[PDB]
Image 1 (cartoon, helix red, strand yellow):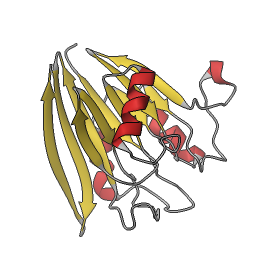
Image 2 (cartoon, rainbow, N blue to C red):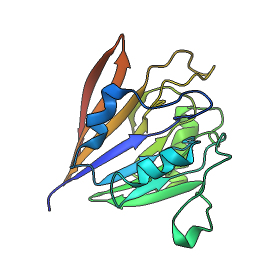
Image 3 (cartoon, rainbow, N blue to C red):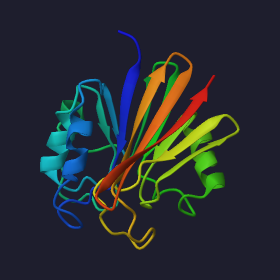
Length: 193
């Protein structure tokens, strides 16, 4: 039926940098309507791999730099998580990669070289813990930040965050969630064509 709702999430770093997702995010992540998960990597915990796989059928997880104890349960994979993924969701080709391969990290120009390489309309990367949405030349660049608020010196004290992206025909409505001072905030950005 109509539309897709895509969860963009990563850099959990459980158990090394955090033990769990904020409880405040619990029901948001339990919503029935999510039919795609694009995970930027650094899940780090097999238990959390299993949790993310159980959200819905279509769950893509890429390998991050701290992923040392996780196993891809997709049968074709031999337990190996791919370094990058390109997935067609409705009208959009979406690129997914951890981001540590982007040099320098989070560089718009380098990011743009990667969308062109992957030939995608929307590129999703993590690694830096910097929550970000921006458009450049009609392409969309998203970083859902750290879902847990785990520390990285790249973006010290980044809050826990994730994104939920509604795709409907040619319309993108992006909800960006972050947790600050005990309160979950949403910022919406909308894109089309």
